[PDB]
Amino acid sequence: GDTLSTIKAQENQIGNNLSPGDTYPKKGLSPLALNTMDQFSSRLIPINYDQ
Amino acid sequence: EHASTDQGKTVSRATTNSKTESNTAGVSVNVGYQNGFTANVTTNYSHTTDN
Image 1 (cartoon, one colour):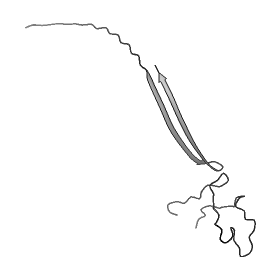
Image 2 (image 1 turned 135 degrees about the vertical axis):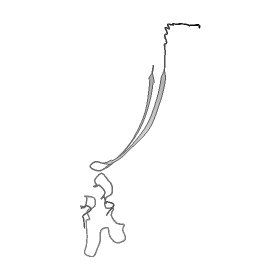
Image 3 (image 1 turned 180 degrees about the vertical axis):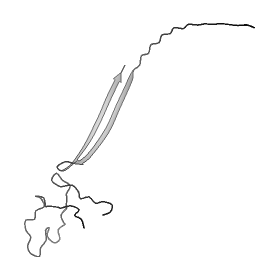
Image 4 (image 1 turned 60 degrees about the vertical axis):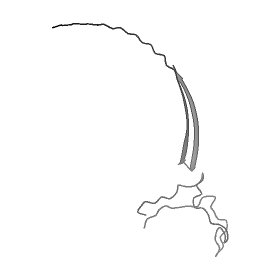
């Protein structure tokens, strides 16, 4: 029931195009890393023991 | 019976001269988060000599 964390796409994770029925990255390409652990990223999302 | 009474008196004097030679070597590894993900590795070595 609780929000672990709220994410917002960094300037390097902005998709230029998204046609209806398409995805970003496109089909066949590998998915995006949510954090990337870089000089731009936010801290990793923590979880308790209960969660 | 035979009864005795001895009394003494000592005077001493000692001089020491020491000399030590120490060497040190260490590695410090740091990882953290500060407006982004950071990392450091420090390598130090020291030499002391006392008389």
